[PDB]
Image (cartoon, rainbow over the protein chains, first blue to last red):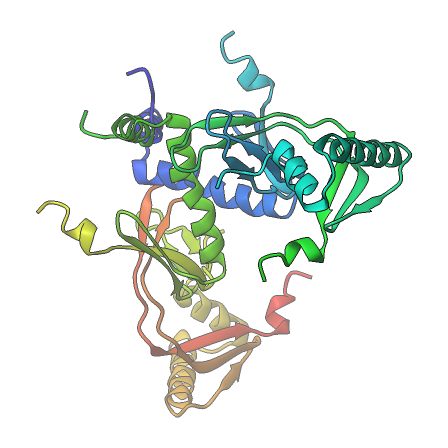
Length: 99
Length: 99
Length: 99
Length: 99
């Protein structure tokens, strides 16, 4: 099929490695806790197959007022305060996967 | 009754003051030019029945995408350049006309 | 297909409601922030179609030592400290969906 | 040389002390029974070359699933009942035999 789902990936890894799928799932899944905990402390993380997680600051977006052009009625956008966001970047092994 | 236009206001003031409409208009035009000249010289002006004219500097604001809140229609709110604006404010004699 | 993915669900809702898929995605996705923020403060959350999120305490599991029965070599399990966990429960509308 | 068995120890002590092996065994058996009786009366005992015998109460521990860490094989670690146990501890004269 065009898309390998996470569950399909766990079965493929299980077959390739001759390991129980539950163990494979546990392993790839244990990464989430490490990554989320690290990013909450502004600690970056590199995971296989070569992806870097960082935290970036998103600048605040002020509130705006406008109008529906067809009806004339006012519309509003609330201010969006500055906040942290997760960024991921492919490292060289992923960038070069097609070679 | 329909909205009182500027032309109807001239006629109603002429009738109340026993002056010709043409004279009333000349007097309001004089007032208009005197307000405009004050604002252009960064000077504030208060007119009866209680309205304050000021000039303010408006900071730039970026474009943001809004929506018709009833329908989900996307509505662009264009960016707003930094600029000088005429601002009017109702003073208490105007605010209280309905009491 | 046997499984409707999240993305497939967004397209189905978009067609049914005659709304842009990006808007549908934004709506169903905005729930995550509300739920995660609430649960981190031990605030429970009920979301459509009728699912209740709560926080439960998992009791600590002590460290254990054992042995591989075939080789005799020691194996160890680290202690797992008591922690909070997310619980979800179906409410009556979901429980009754097949009726 | 091979591990010194209890039987070889008797022979080596007999030779070192110029006593018959049968007498040496009777003496070690007396010591065994005296240690056992002390422990059964909740009494601690120290023997040369420096080993302390105590009785402890061991709290119950639940079953937990382990793994062969090299292969991923699941290995059950059975629950452990609350019980009384004989515990031996090497005192410094034993710990230091290699210095």
